[PDB]
Image: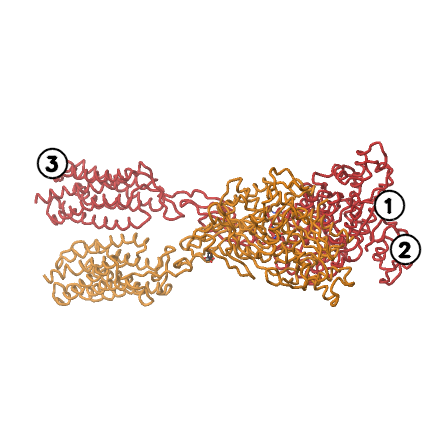
Chain colours: A orange, B red
Amino acid sequence: RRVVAHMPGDIIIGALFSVHHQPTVDKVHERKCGAVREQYGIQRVEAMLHTLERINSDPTLLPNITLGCEIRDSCWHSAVALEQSIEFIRDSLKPIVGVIGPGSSSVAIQVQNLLQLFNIPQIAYSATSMDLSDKTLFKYFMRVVPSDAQQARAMVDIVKRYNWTYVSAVHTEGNYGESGMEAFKDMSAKEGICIAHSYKIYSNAGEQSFDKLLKKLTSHLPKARVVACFCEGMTVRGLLMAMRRLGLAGEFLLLGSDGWADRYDVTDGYQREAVGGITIKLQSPDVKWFDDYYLKLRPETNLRNPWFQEFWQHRFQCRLEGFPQENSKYNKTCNSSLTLKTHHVQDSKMGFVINAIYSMAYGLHNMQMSLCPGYAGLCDAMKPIDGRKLLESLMKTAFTGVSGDTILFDENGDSPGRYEIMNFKEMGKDYFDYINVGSWDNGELKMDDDEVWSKKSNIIRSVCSEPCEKGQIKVIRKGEVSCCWTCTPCKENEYVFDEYTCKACQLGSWPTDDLTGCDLIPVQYLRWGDPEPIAAVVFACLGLLATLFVTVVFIIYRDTPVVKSSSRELCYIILAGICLGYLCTFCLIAKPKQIYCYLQRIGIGLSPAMSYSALVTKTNRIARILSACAQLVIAFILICIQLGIIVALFIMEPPDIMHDYPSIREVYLICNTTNLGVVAPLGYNGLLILACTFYAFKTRNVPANFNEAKYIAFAMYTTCIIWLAFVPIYFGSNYKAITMCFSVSLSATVLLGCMFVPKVYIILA
Amino acid sequence: RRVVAHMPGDIIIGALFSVHHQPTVDKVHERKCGAVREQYGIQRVEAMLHTLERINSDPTLLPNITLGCEIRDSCWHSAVALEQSIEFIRDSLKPIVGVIGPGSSSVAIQVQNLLQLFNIPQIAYSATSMDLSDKTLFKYFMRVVPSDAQQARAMVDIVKRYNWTYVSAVHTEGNYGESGMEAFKDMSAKEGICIAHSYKIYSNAGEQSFDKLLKKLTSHLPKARVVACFCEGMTVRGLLMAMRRLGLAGEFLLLGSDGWADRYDVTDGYQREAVGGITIKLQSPDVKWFDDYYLKLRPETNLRNPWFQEFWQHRFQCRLEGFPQENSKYNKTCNSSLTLKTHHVQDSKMGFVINAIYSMAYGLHNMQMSLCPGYAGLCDAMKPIDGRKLLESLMKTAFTGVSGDTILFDENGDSPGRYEIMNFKEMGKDYFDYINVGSWDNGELKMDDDEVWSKKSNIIRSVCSEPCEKGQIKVIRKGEVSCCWTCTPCKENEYVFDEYTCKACQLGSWPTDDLTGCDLIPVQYLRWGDPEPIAAVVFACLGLLATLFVTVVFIIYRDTPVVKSSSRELCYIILAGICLGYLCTFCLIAKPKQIYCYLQRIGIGLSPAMSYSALVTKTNRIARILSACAQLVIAFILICIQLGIIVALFIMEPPDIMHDYPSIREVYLICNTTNLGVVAPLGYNGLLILACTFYAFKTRNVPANFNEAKYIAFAMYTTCIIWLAFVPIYFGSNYKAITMCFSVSLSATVLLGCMFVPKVYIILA
Ligand SMILES: *[C@@H]1O[C@H](CO)[C@@H](O)[C@H](O)[C@H]1NC(C)=O
Ligand SMILES: *[C@@H]1O[C@H](CO)[C@@H](O)[C@H](O)[C@H]1NC(C)=O
Ligand SMILES: N[C@@H](Cn1oc(=O)[nH]c1=O)C(=O)O
Ligand SMILES: N[C@@H](Cn1oc(=O)[nH]c1=O)C(=O)O
């Protein structure tokens, strides 16, 4: 039978403390507990005994009634605690009025499911799972610590403070780990944080299980460098031991939980592996009087605590001869010089443990105040202490704590509390410590970024993909969590619509700077500058100068017989046409406008048709003579025919500015001239040429005034070749305007020359 | 205190049945449970009370000993069953040697946690959760049913059989539901399925909770019409009542589980809302001998069942006056003609229950054979029947069940089984029934897709997005779920790499039909024939005919005095040049090959070089005379110079066919004749032409033999412009071959016809 610590009194309060370690994986069925525990074990039993004797000593608390206790060992296992709890309720089948419940959430649940049936209030000090807040299933459960709803929030705040996104989660199998990791997963996923993969493990699992878990964790090593452990202390120690076994000394940052806190017994010997880990610890000041009472204990006199001599021997590895408990396993003997004052480490949850004992005390006081206000003691109205009344009194009680605050329970049975942030750092050489690098209260996280990462090179941000909003490149998912993206650049005509897709611009549009939006690329006109068209305009100007010189010479020598043989009007009509060619070239090269672009048509129609019409009549007259003024009229009508066709093409295609986009980039504006709108006048001009071919062959060479027929027959001859050669370039090209300009002013000069010069040259000579 | 059914015996076996319904949410703390049950309650009580008689009347099983029982009421509740289990184990503080576990997985876990402390084996008949298969924590627990693992697969198979991709998930709060939904989520997300959202709810929740759950379920209604309930019977009934309240009559198809099975009590009164639902039932044939005993039971004689009178009054709504259990709540009085034969339904899991007790019988039989073979009864080494030995002999028991099959426990305490897929249909007019429409066994899902949906217009498949495999389009996930995608059309250039990305083809390439792959586009070239080459080659052929005619006239009249002039050999060189130029095109306008394109450049380089150089020498002699046979010497060398440049341009750029791609759509092939490879021969030719233009202008009009020098005075004067006219066309175009073809023959023609034809002319004259 398991041993039990007793203390007499009028009212007896049960307490479950984990004096011994959890049963090993291969001895769960035997329910055999491992080694004794100091922080979680003997210290808590001593705290309970001393605080109860203090309560008995205090006259102002529970006067004239002495509080007893029955402390049992829970071994941090569900079955052992369940059997001890059955032992608690055995009399109810002096009764236990209340239990200072176990420190594990799963164990607390298992004990509560049994205690609630017999109306036994249970006050926990370390069980912090959210599930215990449900008063429908756990009516007889209270705690002096906050739930894990705030601890998960604190962990999420820590991960979101340091840009950590792609973390990996581990939690111990059990209610505490399960609930905590569920809360963390829920809160983090709503705030952009990410989980590579969530793992679970038992605290008592063998070395092989931890090795496998660490292998799975290293499977994401380059990217998921932060591990979030809603783990217990022994789970974290197992992870550290795995790191030691398979050579890992800084590949991970373990973001611990309340289980780890600042426990020195999870990093003993493995400090090098745990350096840089961040943990969350329930805020609890050191208790002075407990330290004063505890360090003065000796195994010779400490007979109340049945485990104490065993503790002595396991702690100071030695054996105590003059006692039953010798245990020769330990070679040497315990000299009367050992004391607990050396390397003494008070457990973090020592404030809470005492508080949970005061609660059940104060809750018993208040209930005694109401039941029998006058009587100072155990009144006859209190012989069968009622569990329901005691629970009610505990729910509405409030008292000053050991720390110096007020402990009180809300409607959910929980109690207010704040958290502390610790960083396990290497302070000196071969010396490590937990350093307080922040806190967390009522939703407000106030860290200290200087103490942790005393440099600008903090831990590599746990991210899956680098920030890739770098202009052209967009972000595409890969069928996994919306966490790890591949970055793809869209084409040049596409701009980023969102961070997720890239959208093409319009027909004549181009994306702006930073590809945030788009832009209608400006139209391109025929510029007056440039090296090419300046030559064309210079040529046109020279042609105009030649034409004005020609007209001056023609009018000065007006009535001379050497020029008064042919019609003066005919070779003034030709002059008007040759001038109109240059005028058409000049008005062609400009901004294509609703006022400008139809002059192109009139030029290209009349100029290369009307001049040849005036010429053909003269050639025919000279040929057939080898008449009168009537040849003028037949000339004019020959113009009018062409004047029809242009007008014929004017109706179907009105003068407008049409935009063409030969490529997706450049935009051009030109008049609406089409394939049919340039061939028909050119077709007629071909006929004009054809007409004069007839004559030119017939005339050939004829001795006239200055042998005009010798030269006028040749000006046409050099024109038809260029007219034909112009077709291939014009048909396929992007330079229609300049080509038209050069064509017109080319066949132009030719004519103006032999037409007039041969005559007017020698005339002036 | 609660009542309990008793039967005396040497060995006592307890049981936990939900005789009454779960306590309502407003009376859980009092632990008073609701109305009586027929299938899950009284029927199983009578099953135990008669199976024990059947065993006790069989000398072949447990001879000369009697099996008593202590049947307790668990009210389908964890707390009530834990209290009753405390009552069971109170003796160990006649002992209970083992129990028939409760029907609920959570309740089974709770009672196992207490029973394993006292080595009391527990056998379950419906506790199907896969949590209890862990023998580390649940050693003394066995069951005659498979795990939920198999059942979750059965569902996954069902959902993947009917294209159902986007479904909703609901499970009952507890272990059964939670474990089942975890398994289903795992093996569904792994294969192809996507869950819109997973919900949970307690069975004993209020109306408002179920209404809220249904409101959340209709949030995804247009897409996810299928809800997967790893829920309990009463959870499904609550869902149906919610559907009735807010007017849903066929928006959802409920995919139920073992909880639902073919229970008429979950779909009574609410058939309209459940029609079409598909449920999974553990297969167990109805035990025939149970009916012939049960149906003849009467409340007058059945005194050993404390719950029989309550049930009898609850079933036929009336009162039994002649009995203490009057229950004056009802109005009328039961006549002595009411029988259980009317509206009798035996529960699905009756055989299981029976087999469970049989499992305990043989375990208690195989023990007594092994412990004391000689004795027929309770031997001395068996008076304190060992729980450990009972469990050991139980795990290895193989026997025959009431169904006729063989019952045997695996290494984890489970037993094999198969599933029946049932469909709730409207058979007649106002008549609804469950129809067996399939089965599932070890991975084989047999089903009858015609009994359900006797048509092709089944339930609108629970899908999110329509298929995107419409050729060009591809799938884009927005970072929501992996089953709701948009369709993006790829451009005509790229081909679909996978379902989710499409990548561009090679620059010379094109996607094949259906965008499945990319194929090599065929190359184009200037084919023999065609519209323009058929006109171009006519020029070359006519030129060759003219050149042969002219050379015939030249060689015939070589010695005629009328040609005794500037060396006829020099002009013969020119004529050979024209012939070479005419044959240049025939190796130019063809299919590009190394043989053709190592001579094309030679031709263009030399043909307009050597002929023109010989013309230069001839005109040089003519001009300087106003020499001897050395003219060839000063001529020939010039040719070499040009040849040198060609050779200079041949070494740097070897003749090879390279593929030119004006755009992605078109492909051509041509040799490596580049811009730099054309200017240099053209530069030399232009320099030569300009050099001889001076002498051509010097000659002008010189009276020579038959005006020989006159024609070449002006004919050459044309060869400049046409060559010049060739320069732009060759630069900006895609027809660089045919342009060269036309230009080469167009140059010679003139020079040829005006230096070798006037000759033929006067030769004839
Ligand atoms: C990322 O963390 C840094 C501090 O390490 C700080 O800038 C901030 O918390 C995060 N960055 C942004 C842009 O918020
Ligand atoms: C969807 O289900 C049908 C029959 O229910 C069958 O074609 C197949 O299982 C699914 N469709 C495809 C294309 O796989
Ligand atoms: N917070 C834990 C309690 N706890 O876990 C440890 O590892 N130490 C410790 O006190 C729980 O809620 O169970
Ligand atoms: N199979 C369930 C139990 N169960 O719940 C019901 O509603 N019916 C029923 O048999 C389980 O494994 O817990």
Which three-letter amino acid code belongs to the residue tagged 3?
Answer: Cys
CB under 8 Å between callouts 3 and 1? no
Q: Chain of mark 1?
A: B
What distance separates the C-alpha of mark 2 from that of mark 1?
33 Å
What distance separates the C-alpha of mark 3 from that of mark 1?
151 Å
Tell me if I can see residue A625 in this picture.
Answer: no
The residue under label 3 is B629
Single out the mark in the foreground, 3 or 1.
1
Q: Earlier in the sequence, mark 2 or mark 1?
A: 1
Q: Chain of mark 3?
A: B
Q: Quadrant of residue B200?
A: bottom right
Indicate the quadrant containing the C terminus of chain B: top left, top right, bottom left or bottom right.
top left
The residue under label 1 is B8
Residue at (13, 67) in percent of width and height: A556
B246 to the left or right of A447: right
Residue that protrudes farthest toward the left in the picture: B626
Q: B636 or A7: nearer the eye?
A: A7
What distance separates the C-alpha of mark 3 from that of mark 2?
151 Å
Q: B434 or A418: nearer the eye?
A: A418
Q: Position of residue B731 (x, y in %)?
A: 28, 49
Single out the mark in the foreground, 2 or 1.
1
The residue under label 2 is B337
Q: Quadrant of residue A142?
A: bottom right
CB under 8 Å between callouts 2 and 1? no
Q: Position of residue B733 (x, y in %)?
A: 31, 49
Mark 1 falls on what kind of element? loop
Ligand 4 within 8 Å of the CB at mark 2: no
Q: Position of residue A596 (x, y in %)?
A: 31, 66
A286 to the left or right of A361: left
Other residues around mark 1 within 10 Å, as few (<14) / some (14–19) / many (≥20): few
Which three-letter amino acid code belongs to the residue tagged 1?
Answer: Pro
Indicate which disc residue A509 carries.
none
